[PDB]
Image: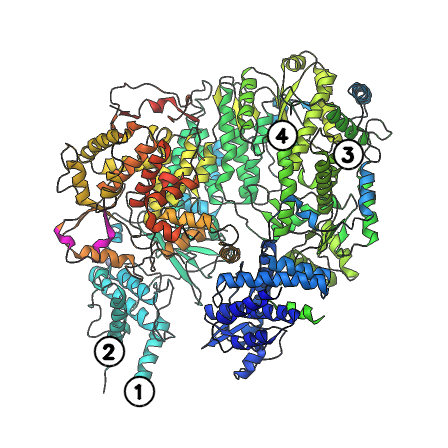
Amino acid sequence: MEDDMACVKDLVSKYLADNERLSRQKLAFLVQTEPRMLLMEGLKLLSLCIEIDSCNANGCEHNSEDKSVERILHDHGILTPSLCFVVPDGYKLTGNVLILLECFVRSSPANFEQKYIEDFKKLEQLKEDLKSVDINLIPLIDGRTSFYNEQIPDWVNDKLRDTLFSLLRYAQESNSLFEESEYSRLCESLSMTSGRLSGVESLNVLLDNRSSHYEEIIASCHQGINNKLTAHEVKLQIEEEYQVFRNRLRKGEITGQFLKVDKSRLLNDFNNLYVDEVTATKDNIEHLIYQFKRASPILRFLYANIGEGNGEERHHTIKECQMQYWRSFLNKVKSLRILNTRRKLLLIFDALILLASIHDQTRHKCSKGWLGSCFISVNDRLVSLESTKRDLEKWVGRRQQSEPPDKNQILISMFQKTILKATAALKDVGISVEHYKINMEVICPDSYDLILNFDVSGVVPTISYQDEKFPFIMGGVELLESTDLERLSSLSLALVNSMKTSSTCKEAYCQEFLLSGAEFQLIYQKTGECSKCYAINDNRVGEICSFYADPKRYFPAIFSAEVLQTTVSTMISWVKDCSELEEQLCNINSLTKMILVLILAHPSKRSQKLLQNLRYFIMAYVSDYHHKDLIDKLREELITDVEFLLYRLVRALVNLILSEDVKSMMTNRFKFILNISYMCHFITKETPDRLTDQIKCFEKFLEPKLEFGHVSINPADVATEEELDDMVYNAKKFLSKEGCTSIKGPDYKKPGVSKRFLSLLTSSFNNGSLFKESEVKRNCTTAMLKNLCFYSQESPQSYSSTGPDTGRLKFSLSYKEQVGGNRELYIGDLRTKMFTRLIEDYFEALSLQLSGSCLNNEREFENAILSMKLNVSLAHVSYSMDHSKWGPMMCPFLFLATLQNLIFLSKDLQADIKGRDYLSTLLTWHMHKMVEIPFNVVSAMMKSFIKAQLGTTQSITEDFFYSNFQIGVVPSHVSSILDMGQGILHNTSDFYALISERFINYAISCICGGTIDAYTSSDDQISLFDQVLTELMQRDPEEFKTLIEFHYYMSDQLNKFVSPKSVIGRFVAEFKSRFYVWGDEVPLLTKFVAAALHNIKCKEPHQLAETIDTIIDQSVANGVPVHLCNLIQKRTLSLLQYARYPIDPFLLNCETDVRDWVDGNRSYRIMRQIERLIPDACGRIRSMLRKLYNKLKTGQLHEEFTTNYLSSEHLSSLSNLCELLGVEPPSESDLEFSWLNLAAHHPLRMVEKVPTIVKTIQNKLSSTFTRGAQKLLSEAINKSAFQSSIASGFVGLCRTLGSKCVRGPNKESLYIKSIQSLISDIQGIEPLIDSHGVQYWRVPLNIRDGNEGVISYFRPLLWDYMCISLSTAIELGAWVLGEPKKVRVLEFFKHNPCDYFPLKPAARVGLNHIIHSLRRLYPSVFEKHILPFSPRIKFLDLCVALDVNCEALSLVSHIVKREEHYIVLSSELRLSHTRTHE
Ligand SMILES: [Mg+2]
Ligand SMILES: [Zn+2]
């Protein structure tokens, strides 16, 4: 064992770089002889090489002397106060930039993430401490997952660490210089293989230490449970229980929780729901219509009468005088950076704008841009007039007397110098100044005297902070028109735009809009994105109105003025043929329109809840039985009068619709009311306030634990007995529920489980009664190591009864937004998630072994839908139920006690025992978790206590804080037993619900003479009854009710509570929000419309099109008509056009029909759009494509096309492809058509080049653990620091498109306007626009040579058309290459809007195939990018080739879940197009 020393010493002597830092450690190692010292020196040298490579690679100076940061400052003469203990590994000072380069090496995922979090937090803290120095700090962290470096080659380093390991184990077995813990740590660190190599058996590495608590818990689980009874000895207990329950219920001690339906009583209870303020029951429609148009200033302004303009004054409002041009130019100039703008380079701008205004004024007498005595400045300001005159005279007098000259001369000199500077700086980058239509004529020879001799007259524009004297007439606009929607759209656009203004008559900001004639000004006095006061002003009469709205909630109505009208119009057409509703048809329209406008004008949470609570009422109205505590659950607190008006409107509508004397069509009215109820999705999803929601969520979390009487406050890591005995005591108490055989009788809605029913369930599962036929068949060295960079310290060594030795599991609490209420959310670390995943997937597999669940399986959902459809068809009884408080009422103790009593059959009995031990240990771990209290809530509670302690309601949580606040304690952590991890433990609860419902159905079947089917996914259940029970319902109304009450009691006995929103009935069935009726179908139109409306994000404009396309494709399959989708697409295109972005024929197709969504796919619509653009030329290519596909189907060439033509020039090759056959070639003025691509060199900027397939491959490949360690966690940390909304996203998108957002040939940035200017320079190319607007250009052939720097952006059309067409024809049938034609022969019928028809589309792939094809076809790229990391594949090769060579959009030809079944209007299919495959 000594020759190894010699050879490795020689190898390291010959393979070490000559560094003045490395030679020291090299000689210190080479001089040593003792093996232990060799170990130390080798480890030190390896660490040195790694850290020096890291320090030199990132361009920094290495800290060899190990000096602290304040030392580094003091040596450089930088004086700083005292600081904490910090040592930088790499430090650099460059100007005012400071660089720190701490680094380390880790192999385990959990260790890597923990070290990253630790040093990141430490360095952020130190950055905060050093911010006072007035010097910037930027940390840099490098964490590598391997020992490879630069100063040493790989093989010598590997053999070095290997021989080091061998000598390590030798010396450990010889001298035992190390103890067990450090020795094991060093082995696991330098092993580089023990990071992650095992699975479930990893728990076998540690020790047990399970001394006493485990035995007590396991015994308490087994105390009084009997799980050996036979099938004969459970029926008797069931019968006895039923007998005593029925007797005690009939006597009058058991209450009963169900009533029979009564429509009149239900309506009468709904009408008198808020009878304390609305002191009436009836309301005339006319008075409501009258007082609706005068409620709020917004509504008054919406329906007022403002017809300013006699017909010629408004004509000038489309002239675009010089003032606006000067304003835009000055804004664009100020967007750059010029020096010394403080009170010098700003007054000049106002002077120029004022001169331009005077010039525009005294030539044709226009009155724009003014407001009383004020004008709009460069930065959307509202500067006055006189103060500017004073500043101007002061400045000119000072500058003149600083020095014969003349005032006008000084003014024109200053103006010309500044203008020359500006125009030079502008010409510098990419743009001339002649494209702004500005002229240097407003600078008259005499201007100062003109400034000093101006005057205006008007009013003062004011703002009032709260009688209302409106300057106009209140209401004169009919509801049937579409004017209020346009006014709302314009006002909302102004309100959203009001957020763009940046920070620095006090100061006033103004935005401008105009409806039809004159223009109005929205005035505000504060920046930022927050609630603030707004006013509306006009030049004739100022201060029209003022209000207190919030900006970020007014998005869904921007350009969607023609979309909502069609929505209401098509929703009305449903209830149109009711023979007893014609006399009341305008009232319905008025009410619907008023509700929509009102909910779009004042968005609030209370209106959302009130509108959401209607579906439960409409479901109960058409059923047989319902919970007794239903009506009381439909009431909530309302505050403002707008909400009361909304409630009155809803009441009037629901009384008009579901009155008496109507018996024609119940399904249509049901669908109508449901769609009305689903309008709550139009408001928003985000929160109005943040602190109150946190307080509410914490209150909901803390409430149900203060009556069970078990809350731990700040538990210690070393658990004391005072907590363990209490845990055991409460665990015993949890299993002490009585019922039906006691003195006090049963008690409802209390957490707990009874021993009798647990025993019954376990015994019935063990002996076998719940399986179908198809189921039974299946010490200085320590500090030395601490100096190292790869010696980890964050691995567990032994577990216990309360988690690993590091500490009990910890979680953080936070809310998640949702329509209506807000959901709770628990967040854990990575090791915790890795630990929980074992239980999760074990229980998921165990449940998959059985049948009936519908959580993640996708086969059972179709069976459920089929059974529901059949049951509804046969008019049987259906029970739709949801459970209440499912999360905070379950318990891991219940799952453990259930698992500890099941007996399996020949399932690796010894491994079965070992797995049971593992699972029991993990569940015992979960039972002892801890949850963190947020910081804002405790801070606010402390502030409130201090405030209202020295100077009533006393919410119980506030009482808890006040109690544990005054004795010297501050709550930080809270632990208990009653709370199951919301969303963490999910599949186990699904399994438990499955077995529980199966046992309950078995018992109910054993009592009566019928059977039941059930379906459930962890919180929702649908039960289907047979014919016997359905007959029993209407023959003996007493046995039915008793059976239902017994089902309720049984479910309560097993810790499952039925919510008051469940329903038993025969008319409708619902599961997972999917309603079904016998002779119709129920689409949710408003839901999909509202979902599609506000669903945009700030990204590249070619992915929003994909997202909207997928959304519309998903929505069409449910019943939405097509023209609505066309209008939605038009709205999206207009939203894009507003941002000044050129529209190309590869975004959307707003001319589709039914067939384009059923049969075709994404590429078919693009092909159809291109065919619509340029006909008379696509047929010639289509004939050649037909012939080529017919030839290639038999596999004739497959190679001449693959390389010779595809991988060459485009134009000439095309011609050859025509002479390869006997078809006529394309004309010379056919290859002239071309479009414009901005991403021809690199994609656009947001905040070499290779195909996108390479991008996604290197993304999905270099991310496992080692090739994707740093980047993913870095980007996650970066994204965690961002919080945004939809409006802010649209604003950011509008901002980025117009700054640079463009890259040049080599490396540079430009502007879009510059590109369009250079394009418009050459007067030989012709643009062309279509109706909806799609720009495409015609360019000649000769003009290309001579200026090849701007023509490198264009791209021909026929080439891409052929690529996409051939690709999609390969992907689909061969009919695509036919010739389409509309059907113009069928006559016109009279259709009803409610008539549907089903359809099926006209009908694996892996990641290795594309790699192998790219290898065997394109070896060049493969050997440099993929190497460092029969009939079916024959066409896959062609697919990937077409994808690589034609990169416009054909990527989607391979990136593509897709629905199958379609339900469409039968009146639409008979007007589609036909494609013939001949
Ligand atoms: Mg349900
Ligand atoms: Zn004018």
Where, by quadrant of the figure, is residue 175 drawn? Answer: bottom right
Whole-number angstrom distance, CA of label 1 to CA of label 3: 96 Å
Q: Amino acid at mark 1?
A: Gln
Q: Is mark 1 within 8 Å of ligand 2?
A: no
Q: Which residues are magenta?
A: 1342-1357
Q: Height in image: 350 above or below 827?
A: below
In the rendered image, the residue lying farthest to the right is: 743
Reply yes or no: does residue 778 show up in magenta: no
- x, y percentage for residue 687? 55, 49
Instruction: Compute the Cα span from label 4 to label 2.
Output: 89 Å
Task: Give the residue type at disc 4.
Answer: Gln
Q: Position of residue 73 (x, y in %)?
A: 54, 80
Which of disc 3 and disc 1 is earlier in sequence? Answer: 1
Q: For numbered disc 3, what is the local secondary structure?
A: loop
Residue under label 1, please give it: 401
Tell which circle, 1 or 2, labels the residue nearer the N-terminal end: 1
Query: Looking at the figure, which quarter contains the C terminus?
Result: top left
Q: Label 1, label 2: how many angstroms apart (C-alpha)?
A: 16 Å
Residue 355 place in picture, x, y as percent? 26, 68
